[PDB]
Length: 40
RNA sequence: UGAACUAGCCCUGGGCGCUUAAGCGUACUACCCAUACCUCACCGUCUGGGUUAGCU
Image (tube, rainbow, N blue to C red; front, side):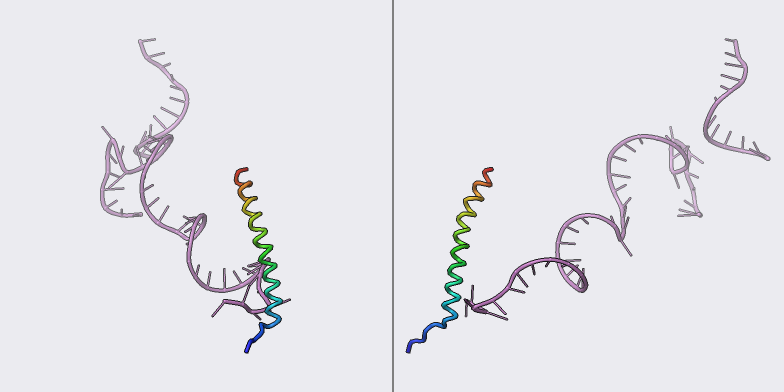
């Protein structure tokens, strides 16, 4: 009755989740550096 | 008082027309338009880059 998600989907989701974390982490830093650069 | 000299125009030796030019010299602003220059679109060629746990 319950169809488990494919295991390749779980592996891709873990990889995509990690890549999104780096993008967001390097996006808040990008905003701060841009504000400091623009003042300079 | 003149004398010559110097330089330049005139005479003798594309068409229509032009004469303080529509010729010649110089200066100055306007204007005309090439397949050239600029901006854009499109064609093609070349060069460089991206694109797969193929993510509704």
